[PDB]
Amino acid sequence: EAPNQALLRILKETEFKKIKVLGSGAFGTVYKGLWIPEGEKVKIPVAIKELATSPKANKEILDEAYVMASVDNPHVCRLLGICLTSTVQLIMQLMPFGSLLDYVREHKDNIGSQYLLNWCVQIAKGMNYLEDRRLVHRDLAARNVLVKTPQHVKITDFGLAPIKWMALESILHRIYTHQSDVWSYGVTVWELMTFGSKPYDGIPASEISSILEKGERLPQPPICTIDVYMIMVKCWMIDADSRPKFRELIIEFSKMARDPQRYLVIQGDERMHLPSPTDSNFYMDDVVDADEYL
Ligand SMILES: CCC(=O)N[C@H]1CC[C@@H](N2C(=O)N(c3ccccc3Cl)Cc3cnc(Nc4ccc(N5CCN(C)CC5)c(C)c4)nc32)CC1
Ligand SMILES: [Cl-]
C-alpha cells in the first residue's frame, strides 16, 4: 500500500483559546474556540477535543488523529493539528451548526427538498471519497454528519475501532465493507427524510438480525416519492453487490436534486428558508474559515 505522507501539525496551546464547551464526555471535553497562528493575522474558528491520562485512551485519540490527518475532501472532516499538553488535544475546524441530526430536528419546519437531497449528495461524495481512499467508515449515521453551513456538511467519526444502522453481514459475521457502509447511508437518509426520527423505534436490539433475514426494512417516509424510497431499499438488500455504489448514489441523488419537488413532497416547500451565512448573517472581527486557510 502506498506510503501515507499526511502532514501532522503540532500546535502550541498558547496559539488557541477555548471559549465555550460544546460537549462533555467522561473520556474528554470538546470546546468551541479560536486559533491564532502568530504573525499570520488570522483567527480560525476551531473545535478542541481534550481528554486526565489513561495509557489506552492516549493511544486511541492518536489513532483518531492519525485517520483525521490522512483525509482531505470537502465532505469529510479533517484535523488541523494536535497539541501536546499534559493531555493531548485534537484540533478540528469548527462546524458551527452542530450535527445534522440535531439540525433537522430543530429546523424541521424549514428544511425543504432541495436541502434534503443535497445533503444526500454531499454525504455520498464523502463516502465515495472514503472509498477511493479504501477507508471504510463502519459508523455512518446522521449524528456523525456535521453541518458547517446548512448548505455544506461533512462526515465525522470515521474509521475508528449501533446495530440498527448495521448491514447484515456486519451483524452476523461482523463483516465491515464499503457496501456495508452503503447500508448505513440508507438508514442515514431515512433519518433525514423523517426529519430526525429513530429507526426501528421500540425494538429489541437482538430481533433486528432476523427481522432483516425475514425481509422487513424501515418504513417509507411520508415526504418520500417511490423514487427516493426505492433507492434506500436498494441499500438494504442482503447481497452486498446488488446494493448501490456510493458513486451511483451520487449520480442518482444529484439527478433528483435538479427537480427537488418531483422527488420529495413537502407541504409549503417553497415557503421554507434556512440560514445561509451568505444570505442572512455571519454572526472578534478578523476571521478566516479553516477551509480557506489551506
Ligand atoms: C464526543 C463528546 C461529545 O459530546 N461530542 C459532540 C460535541 C463535540 C462535537 N465535535 C467533535 O467532536 N469534533 C471532533 C471530532 C473528532 C476529533 C476531534 C474533534 Cl474536535 C469536531 C467538531 C466540530 N464542530 C462541532 N460543532 C458543534 C458541536 C456541538 C454543538 N452543540 C452545542 C449545543 N447542544 C447542546 C448540542 C451540541 C454545536 C452548536 C456545534 N462539533 C464538533 C461532536 C459531538
Ligand atoms: Cl443501535
Image: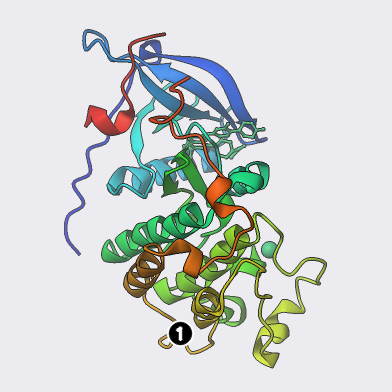
Q: Which one is in front, 91 or 218?
A: 218
Query: Residue 102's x, y, as percent?
Result: 63, 44
Quadrant of residue 258 in the image? bottom left
223 is higher (above) or lower (below) than 290: below
Indicate the quadrant containing the C terminus: top left, top right, bottom left or bottom right.
top left
Query: Residue 112's x, y, as percent?
Result: 54, 52
Query: Residue 218's x, y, as percent?
Result: 67, 75
Instruction: Look at 33% across and 27% down and name the residue there.
Output: 289
Question: What residue is pinned by disc 1?
Answer: 240
Q: Is residue 122 visible?
A: yes
Q: Which one is in front, 272 or 158?
A: 272
**How many numbered discs, if any?**
1
Query: Residue 227's x, y, as percent?
Result: 50, 78
Quadrant of residue 172 in the image? bottom right
Instruction: Look at 75% across and 71% down and name the residue there.
Output: 205
> Which quadrant of the render holds ligand 2?
bottom right
Quadrant of residue 42 in the image? top left
